[PDB]
Amino acid sequence: MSKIEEFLTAEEEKAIVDAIRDAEKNTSGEIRVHLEKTSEIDVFDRAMDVFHNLKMDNTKLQNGVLIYVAVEDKTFVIYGDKGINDVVSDDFWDTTRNAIQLQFKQGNFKQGLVDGIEKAGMALAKYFPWKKDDIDELPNTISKG
Image (cartoon, rainbow, N blue to C red; front, side):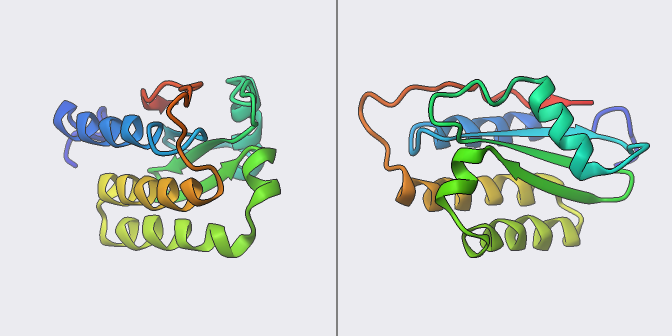
């Protein structure tokens, strides 16, 4: 809070990263978060350039998700790859935004992102159930601008 150099302490980032690792064992899709301060153009186009710049489309099922959050304006954008978008609808995405939006609205960025990942993993698991041979295409480390 007072320190703006680090949005979350190692204890805070440690718990959210662990949540992502557990989701990769519940579904073959991949969820990743990118945190930056403010942009100079549009966040939707900016997240698309960063998502492709980071090669997050390098997945066999094309089911990777990048969460772009602007802590300067307290906003968040969710962009999944063509694989998640082609298999789920806006209604399947609506629960994702309500969980992150409700926690962000309270001021707790970590609880919103962690709870959003949990709901996303169970919802995604319905479309892609975890198989014993499931492979982890993406890491769980948080991305920062």
